[PDB]
Image (tube, rainbow over all chains, first blue to last red; front, side, top):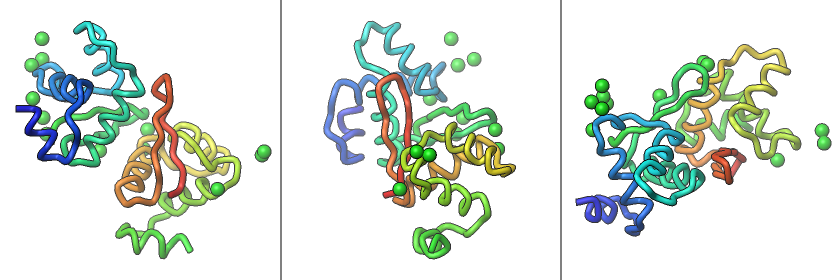
Length: 81
Length: 81
Ligand SMILES: [Cl-]
Ligand SMILES: [Cl-]
Ligand SMILES: [Cl-]
Ligand SMILES: [Cl-]
Ligand SMILES: [Cl-]
Ligand SMILES: [Cl-]
Ligand SMILES: [Cl-]
Ligand SMILES: [Cl-]
Ligand SMILES: [Cl-]
Ligand SMILES: [Cl-]
Ligand SMILES: [Cl-]
Ligand SMILES: [Cl-]
């Protein structure tokens, strides 16, 4: 229940937050960059922009919903905590 | 005093942390991306890697030392809070 997950993390339920959570819950996207998560959203037929993806992920990090990893070469990925 | 800011923020004082705070305090770098901050450090003769810059900035975000902004196109800029 991602509605409950968002409430439990102190965030208003919105479509981008729900759809971003959904992608993070796909096996192939267990770890995902903001750019790849955006591409998956495009593939799904969503119209959620890349800045929104970044904003949501960074809010999720603050809320303790996701973990950020920073790799060599400035490449970054997110996963659910 | 940058040492105090770091200590009160709960972070060990290290040379990269101090150098990163110093770039953020330069008028021209009031707002800067990790990449641009890294470029400036290179210009200063520093040997701080890009992944370290990202890691330090994200720690600074969590400590409430910097504010993060996400612009159109996925551009991710920092400034001191
Ligand atoms: Cl898999
Ligand atoms: Cl697959
Ligand atoms: Cl696989
Ligand atoms: Cl998973
Ligand atoms: Cl894992
Ligand atoms: Cl990391
Ligand atoms: Cl690197
Ligand atoms: Cl893990
Ligand atoms: Cl100048
Ligand atoms: Cl100038
Ligand atoms: Cl300034
Ligand atoms: Cl590095």
